[PDB]
Length: 115
Image 1: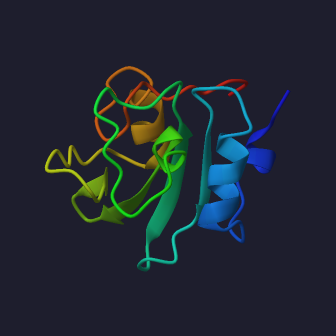
Image 2: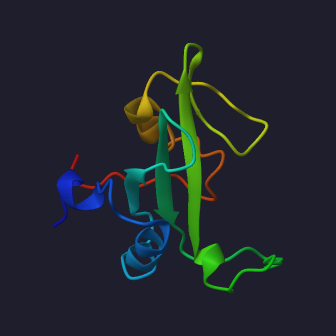
Image 3: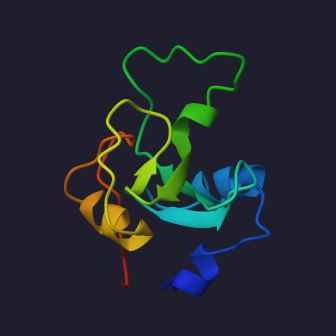
């Protein structure tokens, strides 16, 4: 039984989010203050298992278990700044809800339990 207030932490650091994701059930996600750039939100998602290649670059093998990407919101919509996709959806809620059906940046659809 978890609420958005527990999965939403602006002060929460990236490392903290990764540790909380690797310690929680698969499919769970969280949001934190994106220190990257203004008007950005850090989205973290926990995967069930690593890829078939498992080729981490200067990062522990567990880092792959947790995927964290920074989403930017502009006058053209909000999208995850990391892949060429850039679908540009309505808001964080729009991409979060759609991510549970058509996952792009993430390996698997995002789970939104109790919401």
